[PDB]
Amino acid sequence: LLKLEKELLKQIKLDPSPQTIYKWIKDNISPKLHVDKGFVNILMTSFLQYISSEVNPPSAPSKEQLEQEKQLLLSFKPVMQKFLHDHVDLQVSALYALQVHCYNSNFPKGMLLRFFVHFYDMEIIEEEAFLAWKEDITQEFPGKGKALFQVNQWLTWLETA
Image (tube, rainbow, N blue to C red; front, top):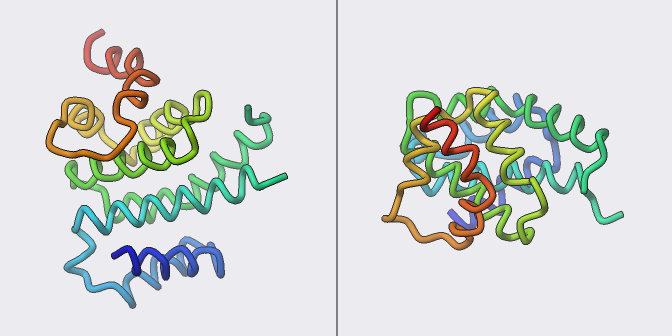
């Protein structure tokens, strides 16, 4: 799975067509793993790494980077939905992936919450998963406090009115 992750990210860089990457998964990863939380973790982690590498390469995002990022995420949305729809616990896994990804970049200003807004508006992550992620004690990935600090007002609104 740490391996699998190696291969998947290599494959995305080689050809980031949503179609190609979905076919590679289906042809190279047993379907029993498609509903595994660790697989959803490596999947979402690889997509986010790729998007970052594209939007903010080694050259405070510009409006052009914000649009580019939305567009790339939009092209991946049907692949992510194919594995996450109807699976709230795997959606919580995808939120931990995005938490750890932002933790790994030192929480860039607004990044985590801009992605929560995306994932919610794109119907990738349901309300229930956002609140399960908030309230979850059982998992231990780093960066959970600083993540909460940045999306708490948003989550509280979601929860109450």
